[PDB]
């Protein structure tokens, strides 16, 4: 059975969730009504009528985003109980999300999660989708993560976190919300996959030739990467078969649980018939910084763990030959206490794309998951922005007025300073 | 449902308020009978923000009309959209405030204030999820000034969890009814600093300057000045009224635009400056120009703490992004370095009436201290000679109230200077 | 008095001595009222423009002209602390005991403002010390409530 | 070059390539924290209300007659 429950919090979490479940349906042959003309039972429950229902919860503090799901293409895919909404949002304020507005819906959200957990006979844990920037994405997620650690003590919790970018962002206070949620979620998360909106924006512009990527364009690319990471949990492979394995394979130091994901190839659907990329070409592209989900320089960092997840027409001996070349021509430095080896997974189904979408259907794809000290650069970027504003106490009054102590800002920043030091200590 | 309760107080408040309703009703396709007749569903998507749904497909402004002078009732009711307003939402006195803040705040205004609050309560309680309040008034008179600020403080104690937003008309000798205007405005600013979340500073000095210097209008009427006010009011409320990912409610706007609780006085701007098609780089340059500001302050003399820019119409969104980033890169010294990415842009497909493209500017600038310095200097010239002080003390006011208002406005000026000189250490 | 009336009021407020003279000769109305009923006399009396007060009075200005609050130019010069103007208005027949809409006499206003020398000249010219404003306060009461010891001694001699 | 952990599944295959070896109920506290925040927010709003109730006493100090 080994079930996994997906939780989508706030606008970013919900919209990425929409793209993920659309792609999961196409991969598993499930129609938008849940009918299908099983390894995927880990993510989809089955009714008496033969209807395949996602083991998913969608939460937002205001109703406009979830109302679009309730009336859209997939209105019959999810049950109404799985789609929870409040009346007033968190207004880009972590304090409203966590304290004043979040406290009003937390018990109802946990009751709905419990209803899905009761349908499980071997619940592995949770996959949590949310932004760092939103008041709900930041504040409500940290409150829910705190409550899930108490109510499901032995269960694994993994995150897919939307890291803010000025090219794609809604708030000047987003660096505050990002540090606040990281501090309060750190001890409650086993593994977190950060998705830098600037990296996704760059890939859509550079590889898909989309000058102005919409949330649809960005989310279809994000869902393609998320699917590459969760495929192992949905198809019964040999690498990352359970939520616990993600921690075992990628996280040797508990606080340093932020692996860098690198995806290839990203090809435009609207481009002339090209010779398909070989295993060697897509593997080489895994060490190209332009293909990363988080902007950072891994040549400045050291590797703790490295997993390569192939999908499609991929011969194991061709992977071995590709990896041999990578250990020669490129300088991949591992920490002196880590085995230096690359863990390999192969899913033989052809990669799936949304029909009529921007992404071209490819013969072979790869997602590399690497735990590198280079990702500390993304923490430094957020911390610097936090520092600039906090030194003047700019915007802090909004948080203090919404059930938060000013001291929580200092406690959060001190934890981030300790995290930056943890990375620096491993990096030598 | 994100409802806003609109309040209009005094002669200025009701005139600019009526013009706001005529302009936004045209944009939303609402005729004076409350019937919808537009061609787009985007017009009705967020109609509930400013309008109540009435019997048989009709829409009624969520507006409360207040004045101590009874003749204001008649003028609004006779206007083109006069009939659109709910008759029980007209709260009018009979004696007037005689351009005296004390009469509006403590005498005539204090007698009418409960009647207004009953109407505010009725509108607020019917809201599915109240965002907050929007008030239109001048600071130079007696009703809008005195009674408006009394109304604000009473609403603040009854609804402390709701946003208080004002469109406050600053007096100028260029457009002046009396010499007691600096007293009325200083006494009001003191109240605004403490009791509003965000204030749009509509400066009559800037309105006069735009009319004469930009359109060469030699004898501007209040109608000529109000054309700029209504264009600005429509622009700054665009993201509240039309489907839009950015600046959805008043709280989210206040959170990102106000770094310090007292520094909530915005310098509005508008482009193109018309009368009763520009390119994206032309709109962008005009929007950041001193000549297009609705507050008589030079942006070049201060630094922007935060900026919001709303572009309206069919235009290249790529061009908007490039142009907005270009202003920040080329003119880095006019934006504080210690609030990263403090310039936010939103684009709305629907342009205002008689325009294909427009841009609305909302600046939280330290340069606004020039407007407060101007009023303070006029207040001090008058107060040192105690000229007309008996008008206020005769209503029960003490001279200490004047001294306190003066100190708090000067404290506000020094606070802006503190952040203008602050370094990103 | 149309454009001349507004121009005369502007020049008396600004203290444009020569511009007031130019406008009189051109026929500007001496008692041309403003929005609050203030004549150029009231404006010169508030702002302390002694020469303008004298030119206006020689050109037949109404020394006892009341604005809409009922204040004559004597009430205003007494409030604003212009001793020399209070002396000139008095010599030109100003009403020492004129009452505004609040019951204030010029003595009420000089006592509240704490203008010791003005109180002395008002009393010399016959200001009634027993006059009560609509709050039921005499000028002696005003000084004692303000805490003005020097002024309460100056007014006790008659009251 | 060394190939360990050769795990063969239904729709997949997995292994390692080692180039070189290493050289060498808390629920009550949640309620107490949310309680504190709520009691602090109320204390903040009650202080704003006392300051406005203070001004109301000053305005009643005018309409005496
Ligand atoms: N990739 C991606 N990022 C998104 C999306 N929507 C918003 N974001 C990002 O997420 C942040 C905004 O947070 P949200 O999740 O939208 O806010 P929220 O959690 O709903 O809270 P409220 O906005 O107050 O309702 C910014 O960094 C945005 O750039 C989306 O659909 N895709
Ligand atoms: N922009 C603008 N300013 C006005 C208008 N009417 C009055 N004012 C200004 O507002 C002040 C007078 O206040 P007002 O609201 O008319 O009187 P009240 O009813 O006693 O508050 C002066 O500074 C005028 O210049 C108007 O229609 N437009
Ligand atoms: Mg939202």
Image (cartoon, coloured by chain):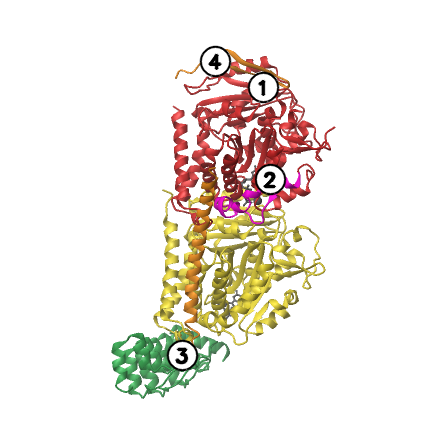
Chain colours: A red, B yellow, C green, D orange
Residue D19 is tagged as 4
Q: Is residue C137 left or right of residue A168?
A: left
Please determine whether, in this image, residue A236 is positioned above or below residue B324: above
Closer-to-camera residue (C50/A48) = A48
Q: Which residue is mark 3?
A: C42
Marking on residue A177: none
Q: Residue at x 42, y 79 (%)?
A: C40
- 4 vs 3, front mark: 4
Residue contact at pointers 1 and 3, CB within 8 angstroms:
no
Q: Quadrant of the N terminus of chain A?
A: top right
Closer mark to the observer between disc 2 and disc 4? 2
Query: Which secondary structure, mark 3?
Result: helix
Q: Where is residue A151 drawn, in percent x and y?
A: 52, 36
Residues at circles 2 and 4 in contact by the CB criterion of under 8 Å: no
Q: With respect to residue A324, does A36 lie above or below?
A: below
Q: Which residues are drawn in magenta?
A: A79-108
Q: Where does residue A371 sit, x and y in percent of width and height?
A: 48, 25
Q: Nearer the viewer, mark 3 or mark 2?
A: 2
Chain letter belonging to callout 3: C
Numbered disc in front, either 4 or 1:
1
Q: Which residue is mark 1?
A: A238
């Amino acid at each position: 059975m080994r079930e996994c429950i997906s939780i989508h919090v706030g606008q970013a979490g919900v919209q990425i969730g929409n793209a993920c479940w659309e792609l999961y349906c196409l991969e598993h042959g499930i129609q938008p009504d849940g009918q299908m003309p099983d390894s995927f039972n880990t993510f989809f429950s089955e009714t008496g009528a033969g209807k395949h229902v996602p083991r998913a919860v969608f939460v937002d503090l205001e109703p406009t985003v979830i109302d679009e799901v309730r009336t859209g293409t997939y209105r019959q895919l999810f049950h109404p109980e799985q789609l929870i909404t409040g009346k007033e949002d968190a207004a880009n304020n972590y304090a409203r999300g966590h304290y004043t507005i979040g406290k009003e819906i937390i018990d109802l959200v946990l009751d709905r999660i419990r209803k899905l957990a009761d349908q499980c006979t071997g619940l592995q844990g949770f996959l949590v989708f949310h932004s760092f920037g939103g008041g709900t994405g930041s504040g409500f997620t940290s409150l829910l993560m705190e409550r899930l650690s108490v109510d499901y003590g032995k269960k694994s919790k993994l995150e897919f976190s939307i890291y803010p970018a000025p090219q794609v962002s809604t708030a000047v206070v987003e660096p505050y919300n990002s540090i606040l949620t990281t501090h309060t979620t750190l001890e409650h998360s086993d593994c977190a996959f950060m998705v830098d909106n600037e990296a996704i924006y760059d890939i859509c512009r550079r590889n898909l030739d989309i000058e102005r990527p919409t949330y649809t364009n960005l989310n279809r690319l994000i869902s393609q990467i998320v699917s590459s990471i969760t495929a192992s949990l949905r198809f019964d492979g040999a690498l990352n078969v359970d939520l616990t394995e993600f921690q075992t394979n990628l996280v040797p130091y508990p606080r340093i649980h932020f692996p860098l994901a690198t995806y290839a190839p990203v090809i435009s659907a609207e481009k002339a018939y090209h010779e398909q990329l070989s295993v060697a070409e897509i593997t080489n592209a895994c060490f190209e910084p332009a293909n990363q989900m988080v902007k950072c320089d891994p040549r400045h960092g050291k590797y703790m763990a490295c997993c390569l997840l192939y999908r499609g027409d991929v011969v194991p001996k061709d992977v071995n030959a590709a990896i041999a070349t990578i250990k020669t021509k490129r300088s991949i430095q591992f920490v002196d206490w880590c085995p230096t080896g690359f863990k390999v997974g192969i899913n033989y189904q052809p990669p799936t794309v949304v029909p009529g979408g921007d992404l071209a259907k490819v013969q072979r794809a790869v997602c590399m998951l690497s735990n590198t000290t280079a990702i500390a650069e993304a923490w430094a970027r957020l911390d610097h922005k936090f520092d600039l504003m906090y030194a003047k106490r700019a915007f802090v009054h909004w948080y203090v007025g919404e059930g938060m102590e000013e001291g929580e800002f200092s406690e959060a920043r001190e934890d981030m300073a300790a995290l930056e030091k943890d990375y620096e200590e491993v990096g030598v | 449902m994100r409802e806003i309760v609109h309040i209009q107080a005094g002669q200025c408040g009701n005139q600019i308020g009526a013009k706001f309703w005529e302009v936004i009703s045209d944009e939303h396709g609402i005729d004076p009978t409350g019937s919808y007749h537009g061609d787009s569903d985007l017009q009705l998507e967020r109609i509930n923000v400013y309008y109540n749904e009435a019997t048989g497909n009709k829409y009624v402004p969520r507006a409360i009309l207040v004045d101590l002078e009874p003749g204001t009732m008649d003028s609004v009711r006779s206007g083109p959209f006069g009939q659109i307003f709910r008759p029980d939402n007209f709260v009018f006195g009979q004696s007037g405030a005689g351009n005296n803040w004390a009469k509006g705040h403590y005498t005539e205004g204090a007698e009418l204030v409960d009647s207004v609050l009953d109407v505010v309560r009725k509108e607020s309680e019917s809201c599915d999820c109240l965002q907050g309040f929007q008030l239109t008034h001048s600071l130079g008179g007696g009703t809008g000034s005195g009674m408006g600020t009394l109304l604000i403080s009473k609403i603040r104690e009854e609804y402390p969890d709701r946003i208080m937003n004002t469109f406050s008309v600053m007096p100028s000798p260029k457009v002046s009814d009396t010499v007691v205007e600096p007293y009325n405005a200083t006494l009001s600013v003191h109240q605004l600093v403490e009791n509003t979340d965000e204030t749009y500073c509509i400066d009559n000095e800037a309105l006069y300057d735009i009319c004469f210097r930009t359109l060469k209008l030699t004898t501007p009427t209040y109608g000529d000045l109000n054309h700029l006010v209504s264009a600005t009011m429509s622009g700054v409320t665009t993201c509240l009224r039309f489907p839009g990912q950015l600046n959805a409610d008043l709280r989210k706007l206040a959170v990102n635009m106000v770094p310090f609780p007292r520094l909530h006085f915005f310098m509005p701007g508008f482009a193109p400056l018309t009368s009763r098609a520009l390119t994206v780089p032309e709109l962008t340059q005009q929007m950041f120009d001193s000549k297009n500001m609705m507050a008589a302050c030079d942006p070049r003399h201060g630094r922007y703490l935060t900026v919001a820019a709303i572009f309206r119409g069919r235009m290249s969104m790529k061009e908007v992004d490039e142009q907005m980033l270009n202003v920040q890169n080329k003119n880095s010294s006019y934006f504080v370095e210690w609030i990263p990415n403090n310039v936010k842009t939103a684009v709305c497909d629907i342009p205002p009436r008689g325009l294909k493209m427009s841009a609305t500017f909302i600046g939280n600038s330290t340069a606004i201290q020039e407007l407060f310095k101007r009023i303070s200097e006029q207040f001090t010239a008058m107060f040192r000679r105690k000229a007309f002080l008996h008008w206020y003390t005769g209503e029960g006011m003490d001279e200490m109230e004047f001294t306190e208002a003066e100190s708090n406005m000067n404290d506000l000026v020094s606070e802006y200077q503190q952040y203008q000189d602050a370094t990103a250490d | 008095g149309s454009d001349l009336g507004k121009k005369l009021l502007e020049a008396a407020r600004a203290g444009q001595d020569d511009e007031v003279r130019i406008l009189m000769a051109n026929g500007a109305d001496v008692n041309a009222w403003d929005t609050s009923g203030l004549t150029p006399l009231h404006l010169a009396a508030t702002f302390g423009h002694l020469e303008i007060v004298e030119v206006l009075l020689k050109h037949g200005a109404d020394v006892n002209a009341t604005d809409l609050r009922g204040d004559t130019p004597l009430h205003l010069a007494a409030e604003v602390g212009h001793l020399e103007i209070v002396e000139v208005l008095l010599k030109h027949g100003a009403d020492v005991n004129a009452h505004d809409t609040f019951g204030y006499t010029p003595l009420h206003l000089a006592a509240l403002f704490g203008h010791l020398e003005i109180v002395e000249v008002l009393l010399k010219n016959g200001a009634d010390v027993n006059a009560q404003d609509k709050f039921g306060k005499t000028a002696f009461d005003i000084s004692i409530d303000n805490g003005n010891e020097d002024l309460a001694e100056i007014l006790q001699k008659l009251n | 070059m060394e190939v360990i952990e050769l795990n063969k599944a239904t729709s997949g295959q997995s292994w390692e390539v080692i180039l070189k070896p290493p050289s060498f109920p808390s629920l009550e506290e949640i309620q107490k924290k949310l309680e504190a925040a709520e009691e602090r927010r109320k204390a903040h709003f009650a202080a704003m209300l006392e300051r406005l109730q203070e001004k109301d006493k000053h305005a009643e100090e005018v309409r005496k007659n």
